[PDB]
Amino acid sequence: GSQTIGLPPQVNPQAVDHIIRSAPPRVTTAYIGNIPHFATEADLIPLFQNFGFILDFKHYPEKGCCFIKYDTHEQAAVCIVALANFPFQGRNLRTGWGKER
Picture 1: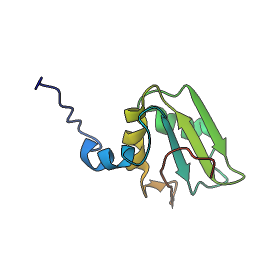
Picture 2: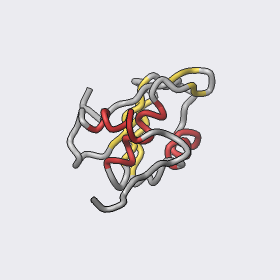
Picture 3: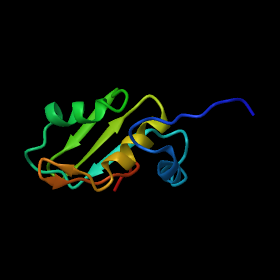
């Protein structure tokens, strides 16, 4: 097999690999729940961008959830595990695959 392995300093593709298995390789959206009312895109959009790229971010403070769209699916898997039960402005957030609900 060709030498193709990605071992980044942050986030692990292993524990994240299981995430993708819970969704199609086509879809590429990161769902973050448990967001405070004082959480705007100005502080969130960039909090996710650092991951890769954001073509469209949907923040819903009225419900406490946001959906970030990336270029590839693997891009969402990274932030997915990284945001998994991660601290944010004192409050922790959630992670998952953008779903109706």
